[PDB]
Length: 11
Length: 12
Length: 238
Length: 235
Ligand SMILES: OCc1cc(Br)c(-c2ccc(O)cc2)c(-c2ccoc2)c1
Ligand SMILES: OCc1cc(Br)c(-c2ccc(O)cc2)c(-c2ccoc2)c1
Image 1 (cartoon, each protein chain N blue to C red):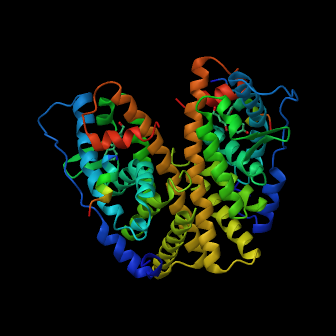
Image 2 (image 1 turned 135 degrees about the horizontal axis):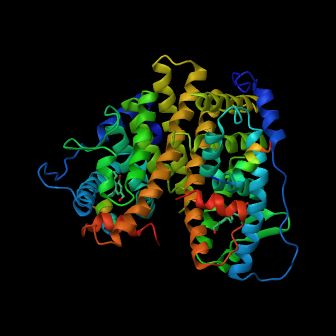
Image 3 (image 1 turned 120 degrees about the horizontal axis):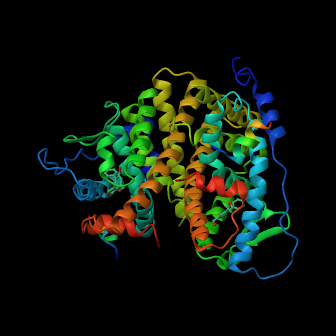
């Protein structure tokens, strides 16, 4: 659950 | 400077 | 898969439209430079650049066709390369200078403010000259940046991989399409293609060197608490 | 004189390169297993040290390499030596999936890489590049062309003749592809796929250089005469 992971997921 | 590489490049 | 369905001209428009803007740094002309402020300027800029890079990657045809796990890996692997080729591109029309930002053009001397930064600057300056030397065009640059993203970590992850290799071929086609249209002969087309991709080897080299330099600055306590950047940095020393 | 390399035709370039190929050397014949961290690193550095001598003789037979000043020659070699040894390792390992053929008598699986700290990560990259070579059906003729490109390209930005020689090799590569019956589109695509591999060889080289320097610091492997100097080349 990296920050990159999140920013990639978010629409 | 002294380098073995120099020796191999020149001796050929 | 709209990706493998794009024509050469649509691929070009897709990539050109996804181009992130050129951001400004916090550079104050009156503030004396130190090792901490210069590193502070670059990391602060890069950190903001990373957000745009993540949103740009999503618009690169085929990228979102990959699992989140693959997307994360490709970006963790290519982020500094992408930032660097972006930096070299911006500095093309400024011989001897690296245009980190519109209000931040640095020369190698200014690079001595940071321990061991000058040799990285020298490599970026040389790559920038190379860009001038062959008159690299904007359309070709966007193709190179997308190639870096898709290629850098493509083997360090098998069907999702096959997908990537097909988009890569679509890009190679687009590069050919662009050259043919510019009037280049077949021979000239395959030679410039090689010249362009050979650049990626140099981009990868500077990236590895700058990643080591950055990690070293992080152990000197001169790199701010930029979570995204730091997280991107740590992914390189598993 | 002008460079006699530019007048060479595709076929003469190809045969000149295959003719320059260095020999394949053997490692120690001691069958003592398993290896320790030092014994492993010792076998590898002893081998590379000996290969570097033949690598140098090979470089001098690369069309257009001797037309460069001694200064440039030295520079190109110090910059690409590890990349060149590695693509050689990847090439020799192509027909042995999941294994690295460092020498005929030194075929290592990825597991044996664990013998050395931080070595397995490098082994995996080399193995993957190797499967990549195998899946593309890399030909020996394409291989010698690629290896020559590393030599001339890696330290070329660090400075027209060299760039004319690279174009020659690029033409030679397409010639080999047209000869293999590849369509125009397949030639360009394959040219791209092959060259993108050099980005990976470079990355592998950077990692292995750092890892090799590490070992040096721990004072383990006996760095040899030429290898040490080549290692030091990277400030
Ligand atoms: O210390 C070595 C170093 C050198 C450079 Br040159 C950069 C840099 C590259 C491109 C860009 O657009 C901004 C900065 C960074 C860096 C990368 C991320 O944060 C800082 C680190
Ligand atoms: O420790 C990281 C490391 C990894 C490898 Br893989 C090699 C190596 C590469 C090609 C070859 O033909 C023999 C050895 C070396 C190394 C040892 C000496 O010179 C290079 C160092």
